[PDB]
Image (cartoon, rainbow over all chains, first blue to last red; front, side, top):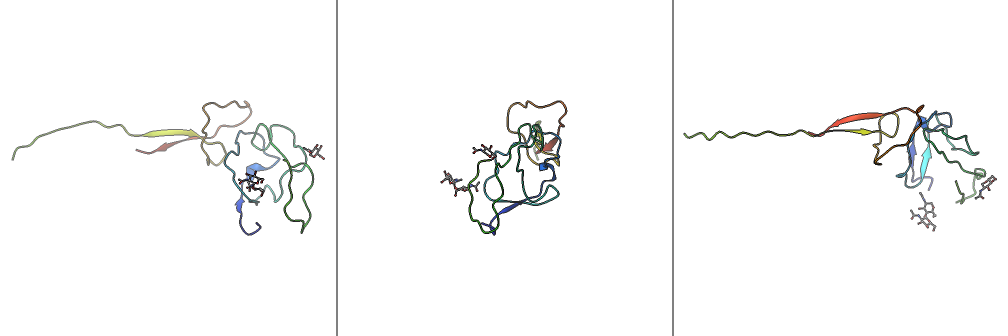
Length: 75
Length: 49
Ligand SMILES: *[C@@H]1O[C@H](CO)[C@@H](O[C@@H]2O[C@H](CO)[C@@H](O)[C@H](O)[C@H]2NC(C)=O)[C@H](O)[C@H]1NC(C)=O
Ligand SMILES: *[C@@H]1O[C@H](CO)[C@@H](O)[C@H](O)[C@H]1NC(C)=O
C-alpha cells in the first residue's frame, strides 16, 4: 500500500490546466500525487474541458480521514 | 584478382507521432483525434534508421 506506489509528477494534471486530450488508458495501480498540481485530486465536478482533457473526472464524496483503511469510491 | 562490383539502394526509417501530453511524453495510438480548436498540438519526429 503506502510503501508500494508510483509517484506521478505532472504539473499539467491541475484543475487549472486549459485543455488537451490525454487519456489514461494505461494507468495501472496505486499512485502518489506529487508536484505543483498538489497532493490530492478533485473533489467536486470541475467544469468541462479542463485538466488537458475534454472530459475530466473527479472523486465524488470526501477523502477518508487518517486511519480509515481501504475505502471504495466511484470517481 | 577478379573484382565483381555490385550495388544497391536502401530506405531509412523516419517517423512522427502525436504526443498526447505536453513535454512530449506519450504517443497517440488512436487512428483519429477529435479535439477543440483552442487546445494545443504536441507532435515530434523520430529517427529509427
Ligand atoms: C484497487 O482495488 C481493487 C480491490 O482490491 C483491486 O483488485 C480489483 O478488485 C476487483 C473487485 O474484486 C476486481 O473485480 C478487479 O479485477 C481487481 N482488479 C485487478 C486489476 O485485478 C484493484 O486491482 C485495485 N486497482 C488498482 C488500479 O490499483
Ligand atoms: C457521488 O457523490 C455525489 C455527491 O454526494 C452524489 O451526488 C452522487 O450521487 C454520488 N454518486 C453515486 C454513484 O453515488
